[PDB]
Image (cartoon, rainbow, N blue to C red; front, side, top):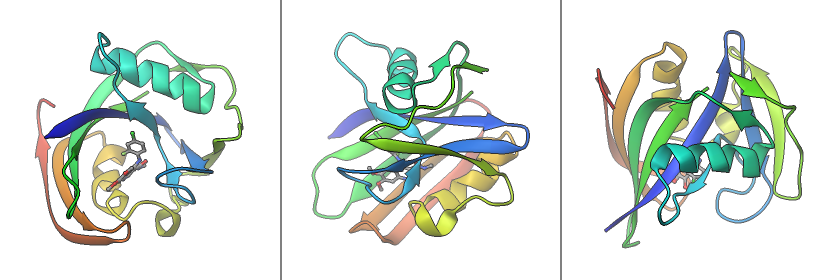
Length: 153
Ligand SMILES: CNC(=O)c1cnc2cc(OC)c(OC)cc2c1Nc1ccc(Cl)cc1F
C-alpha cells in the first residue's frame, strides 16, 4: 500500500535550493521539489517534471540518491519517495505555491524542515546514497526510523 513520489534537491558545491511550501501538506516548511509520479511516466521523468512545476527550473541530468519510505501512523498509504540530486537551467520562480531560496551548506534551516531531513541530509551532502524509512506520528514526531547507506539506490 505505497504510492510513488519524487523529491529533487538542487545541490551545488556551496549551496542548496529549497522551497518554502505555501499551502497543502507540508506548508510552512522548506522542502526539496517533488510530487506524485503519474500514470505512464517513469519515476525520473516525474522528478524532472515536478522540479519544473514547483521551482521553474529545467534539469537535464538527474542522479538518484535515495529512496525513503514515510509512514504516518493510522494512515494507510505509505509514501515511497525517490530522491534525486542535480546541472540546471533557468532561475528559481516564486509562485503562489512555493518560495525558493538558496541556502549555504552550513545554514540549512533544519528547524523549519521536516524532522527526517536532519538524518539523511548529512548523507546527501557527502554524496552518499541511502535507503530510509521514517514512521511519523503527526507531522512533527518521528516514532522510529531506519537509515542505511547503499551503493545502489
Ligand atoms: C528536503 N526534504 C523534504 O523536502 C522532505 C522531507 N521529509 C518529508 C516528510 C514527509 O512526510 C513524513 C513529507 O510528507 C509530505 C514530505 C517530506 C519532504 N518533502 C516532500 C515534498 C513533496 C513530496 Cl511529494 C515528497 C516529499 F518528501
